[PDB]
Amino acid sequence: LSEQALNHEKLMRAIVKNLADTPMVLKGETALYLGYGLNRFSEDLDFDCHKKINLLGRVKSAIPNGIILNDIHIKKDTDSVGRYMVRYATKDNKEEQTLKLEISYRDAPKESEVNVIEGMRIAKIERIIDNKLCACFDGEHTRTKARDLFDLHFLAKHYEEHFNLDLASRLKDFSKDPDKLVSDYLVDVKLDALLNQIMDLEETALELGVMAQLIHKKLEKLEHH
Image 1 (cartoon, rainbow, N blue to C red):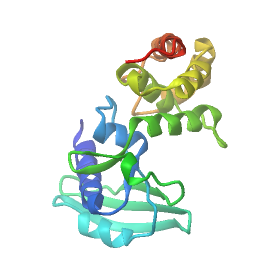
Image 2 (cartoon, rainbow, N blue to C red):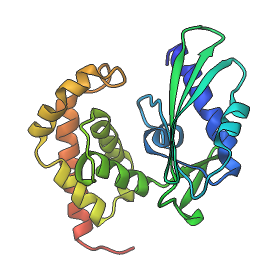
Image 3 (cartoon, rainbow, N blue to C red):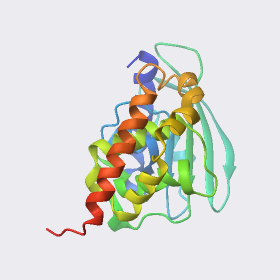
């Protein structure tokens, strides 16, 4: 964890802690990082929220000591989506940084589906798995991002109990051809600063395929406790 990263994290945590008394629910990669022990750094803030709030006002108030807020650019503010570029600097370094902040106002989790971890409102693992699989495999607009392989492996390894039959079946299907995964993701892994040092693509792909196969097989037994 470099100084740039540590400060970035300082900024993210301050924003999410501030939003704890609103309906904002943290999701995605940084939910995993801040909430569930993800073993890579994450940089974006992604939220679901059932209604509009004074987002700008909250971000401004939330800037903690040691951070300089240069600007907030409103990329998109509609009924269904909020998309912002928060530009900032630091007491340790003057070079401008960016934080992407994105909110979805559709299909917000109901209050009974919201976890609180160290004072932060965060989505359940199940929803995060579902969203990742939509994002990398079977959603409306899939993408090829190595982060998704890294994160699904993490989830399959450390949170297998949160997989149900549907989630496991899709995971198994996503990861059935490990050589294709390695082929599909290789360039992205090399170009990703967050992954290129820490990730063995060949091993990750292989282990995911094996873990998914086993998780799904277990759930197919329809066992009870």
